Amino acid sequence: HKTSNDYAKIIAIPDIVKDLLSDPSTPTVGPQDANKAVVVFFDYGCGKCAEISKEINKLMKENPNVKFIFKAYPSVKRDAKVANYASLVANEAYLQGGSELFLAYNKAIFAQRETNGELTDQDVDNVVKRLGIKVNDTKLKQKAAAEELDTRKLGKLIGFQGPHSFVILPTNLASMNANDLGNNVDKVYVISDKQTNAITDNYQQAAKWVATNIQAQLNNIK
Ligand SMILES: [Zn+2]
Ligand SMILES: [Zn+2]
Ligand SMILES: [Zn+2]
């Protein structure tokens, strides 16, 4: 099995674990005292992420005690400026309205993408206006054009090459030191983007496989 990345081993250091689980600016859903977490790397401009998002919505309802953490990873396929902008707006929606406003924004952006076959900056602005999100759109647009997302840098550091990468892990790894964490690499479970892309080209059956696999891993954490 050459050319396989040891994602769990890379993840299992305090710096990366706390970024995955404890970044206050990253949109989350579910209780802060959840014992289990699912980290979703996603791309608002990606049609497959749009199908996956709907399966994740169901997963969150089926697992109300589980924490879901949404890390934006715009694909290196497309220009990232729009997806960057939409992700930066998602951060402001989460800071203002918490999980609830984030989910409404999140669901509405992916609906635009699933519907039109593309995402535009006007799609973001109209969702912003509609849901009453306060943004300095000029500043965020410039940031979207100028910077790489920190959530994308995190995903790249882990070894993911793109969105629909997932990490399922216990939340108590956030309180472990480097020695503790290295003895607990086994508790870090990863569905890589290479795995997700190897499934199929049917977006829906890929989303359903991902959801079924996440549920099993969740079931397997104490
Ligand atoms: Zn084998
Ligand atoms: Zn995707
Ligand atoms: Zn394989």
Image: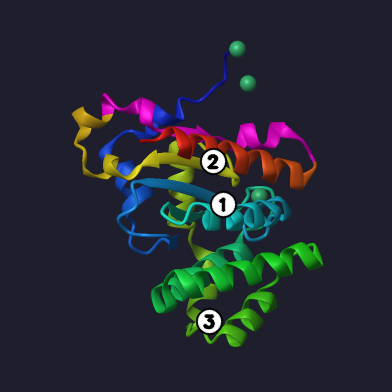
Q: Is 40 rendered above or below residue 14?
A: below
Secondary structure under tag 2 reads: helix
What's under tag 2, amino acid-wise?
Gln
Residue highlighted by disc 3:
137
Disc 1, disc 3: CB below 8 Å?
A: no
Within 8 Å: ligand 2 and the Cβ of disc 3? Answer: no
Q: Position of residue 178 (x, y in %)?
A: 21, 32
Residue highlighted by disc 2:
215
Q: Of tags 1 and 3, which is closer to the observer?
A: 1
What's under tag 1, amino acid-wise?
Leu
What's under tag 3, amino acid-wise?
Asp
- Quarter of the image where the N terminus is located: top right
Q: Of tags 3 and 2, which is closer to the observer?
A: 2
Point 54% across, 58% down: residue: 61
Q: Position of residue 176 (x, y in %)?
A: 21, 38
The 10 Å Cα crowd at callout 2, few under 14, some 14 to 19, many 20 or more, is: some
Point 51% across, 83% down: residue: 133
The residue segment tinted magenta is 182-201
Whole-number angstrom distance, CA of label 3 to CA of label 2? 37 Å
